[PDB]
Length: 92
Image 1 (cartoon, rainbow, N blue to C red):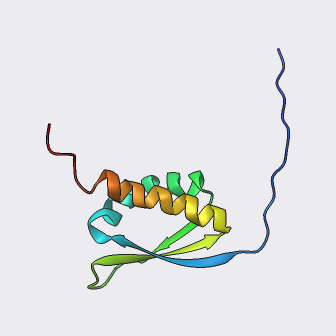
Image 2: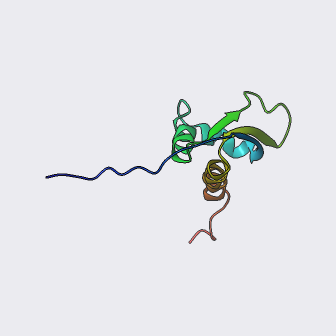
């Protein structure tokens, strides 16, 4: 009983991206203790800095930090949450 390992993994250079999300979802994006978002941060391995108080805007800005491939991956997750929590295809 054995298993391989392999490698092929590295990073370099970090960029900042500005992504807006629906405050009506962000609140749910965080999760219970910020685990819902953590999974997204760990899933895409990207950083997501969400403001404590959106203030009075409809969308809450989220400061992303990390690779570009990670920023997008994370975004997909975010948008997903919103999408998954946007509306159903006519209550069957």
